[PDB]
Length: 247
Length: 253
Ligand SMILES: O=P(O)(O)OC[C@H]1O[C@@H](O)[C@H](O)[C@@H](O)[C@@H]1O
Ligand SMILES: O=P(O)(O)OC[C@H]1O[C@@H](O)[C@H](O)[C@@H](O)[C@@H]1O
Image (cartoon, rainbow over all chains, first blue to last red; front, top):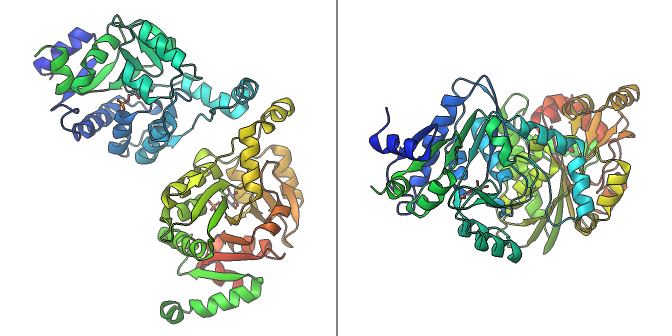
């Protein structure tokens, strides 16, 4: 079963399960690929006959997508982004990762097409539109969520974060981020990126949540994110886990 | 080409060009309805055709569909490093996301190491929602770009197949059936004489606009498309066709 390290991590972070691959992805870049491989195997163990898989962007979930292969059980797979624009560049956007993962899985996918510099009026018009509402409804019915976790400062800087929001993130001592929410050390939301789709309150209804995040630089972010019960499986590496656990 | 010569394609292309009054005909071996690699070979041939026709600066309008996706897949950067901007020819045509022009456009531009501009004007907008969005600077910008397209690369489909693949409202299915549409290109359904009998309403390029595009490349093959290709070319289109033997031989038989 679990190693002592995995067992300790599960207990410390109140995880549904812990999956720890060897090495430190901050040292040892290819370790991110090994997290991806392990995450893909974890997803396959969890699939039901039909599945609606919501995904975030970021480089770690892109590694999940890169390691994705078709399901030998041939279960029904529909992929969607978890949320609309989060300010990421194209290679990091949930829409990009979603399409890549679905293609690799030989599944189907839907995208959220919500710009992106357009007006308030135009914005509200886009989100009321039938095809968009359809995708929003699909995300609301997700059976699985696969998501990254990042350091708050790092993520705020990588994205196109307004200066007033950077100030708010700093002033409120955000230390971690996931799916467009920034959290403090006690895992409480302190700032949220406005975006349609999945909300934090919605994750409780999703049967299988798999977080994929590692590297020693993220040990503090991961600990803080899991300070609240998330009922989540964490795929991580020794770099993060040993640092977090002081081992 | 000696390869084309020995395979009988040089003659077949001459015969097809003359039969359809094409600007030129490019035919690859085999039948894409039977052999999956033949579609990739159409893509490769289309890319060669595009590169031959690029100028210093290019605005390339593209449609969606699996055939133009194959063009995108076979695309490579321009060894001459000419300026390439890719745009979808029209907005939402009711395709699933994989087959949408926006999807093919992005893929093509990435493979060409060019730039792209997408058009997000959904087909199911209310009248009021539409008025709002059409005035957005970002939307006006893309529509304006499309208006200056220097090249169009488009697929051709059987009317019935396309009507079923897109989510076509019942009333429109009836109209397509009642007017005996046999072919489809860029959201227009045409009869056997190449006359428009149904138009999917959508912003961007309209049929009359193709006359101002100096280089138009249609990419479509497989035996199942022989009649559709023949019907589309019943009118002058000033177009180069890339196809396969499957479509060409059947059409010519
Ligand atoms: O995996 P990376 O590149 O460190 O990025 C992680 C972040 O990527 C973001 O875009 C996701 O929406 C977040 O869930 C995540 O925290
Ligand atoms: O290449 P396929 O998959 O046969 O699809 C062709 C059709 O794809 C549609 O999306 C295009 O707008 C048409 O120009 C074309 O007829």
